[PDB]
Image (cartoon, rainbow, N blue to C red):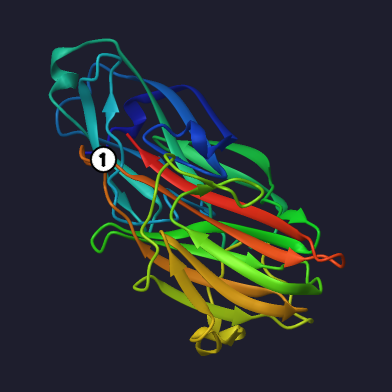
Amino acid sequence: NNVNDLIKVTKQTIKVGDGKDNVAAAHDGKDIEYDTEFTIDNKVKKGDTMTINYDKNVIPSDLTDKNDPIDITDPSGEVIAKGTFDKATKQITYTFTDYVDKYEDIKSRLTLYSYIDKKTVPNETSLNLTFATAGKETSQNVTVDYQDPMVHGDSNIQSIFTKLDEDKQTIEQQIYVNPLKKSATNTKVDIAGSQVDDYGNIKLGNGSTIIDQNTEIKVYKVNSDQQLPQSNRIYDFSQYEDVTSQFDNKKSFSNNVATLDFGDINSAYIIKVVSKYTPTSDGELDIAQGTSMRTTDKYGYYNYAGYSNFIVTS
């Protein structure tokens, strides 16, 4: 059964990484990388188990709970152990394969990726993270830096992905419109099923989603005296005013773009979007969706601010 006592940890580290460096599931924003190197006593045998613990304030993916843990593999890719993840205990239990009966003096390394829990850590702060391999812990202080909005003139916006449902092939995006609570004249918000640059220009060929009349779009108004979580992720929409039906006659669609006519505003809004995506021909994700806010300055010229999210698996 459990052979944690026969696992010696050579080195284990925790850091903040960039999501684009998680090759198996690359994404915008940051993540936590746990890199562990350990030796397996020769006494360990097939079907024996070891554990790895995540920090209580991280989640292996904050987009879905359906993935299995990655295997422990050698440099050639032979499988040393297969894992199962228990959400309750935030622990992986790894079961050694026959690899540990056929090889001796085994060393192994693993990198596990995770996300700060945005419900537990809704705003920027520093905190201590603690992980463990085979019951041996290490700790690391990290600073959590969430993104800034993109700001041009009165145009100011930010977005993140929040929920992937691979059964229905949908992605959820949460967009903050005017989080700075500016007075924004003739505001238009686009949602495009492609990457968008910082000025709202569509950049086709960098991932996609489908944005059309069947995309679910909900819109919430934020009061002057409400501050939005810096994490960009809302867990409880009941605290905001659902104004979705006010947009029934304010939406238009053209060539995989939705436009919402906000008009003259002086408040922040939250848009929650659920859109369909299309897996690639070889069974991977190549998801990208962007948003932009257009406002009119006092001289009648337009300012645009864009934001874009992505998930690309391999």
Q: Is residue 83 above or below residue 23?
A: below
Q: Position of residue 44 (x, y in %)?
A: 22, 24
Residue at figure coordinates x 64%, y 58% from the top left: 158
Q: Is residue 253 in view?
A: yes
Snapshot quadrant of residue 304: bottom right
Return the x and y of residue 182 as percentages of the image width and height.
81, 71
Residue located at (77% from left, 74% from top)? 185
Q: Which residue is mark 1?
A: 83
- Could you say which is closer to the camera, residue 16 or residue 245? 245
The amino acid beneath tag 1 is Gly
Residue at disc 1, secondary structure: strand
Q: Residues within 10 Å of mark 1 (few under 14, many from 20)?
A: many
Q: Residue at x 17, y 20 (%)?
A: 99
Residue 95: quadrant of the picture? top left
The quadrant of the rendering that contains the C terminus is top left
Q: Where the N terminus falls, by quadrant?
A: top left
Towards the viewer: 124 or 191: 191
Q: Residue furthest front?
A: 300
Q: Is residue 128 left or right of residue 21?
A: right
Is residue 121 at least partly visible in the picture?
Answer: no
Q: Residue at x 42, y 39 (%)?
A: 205
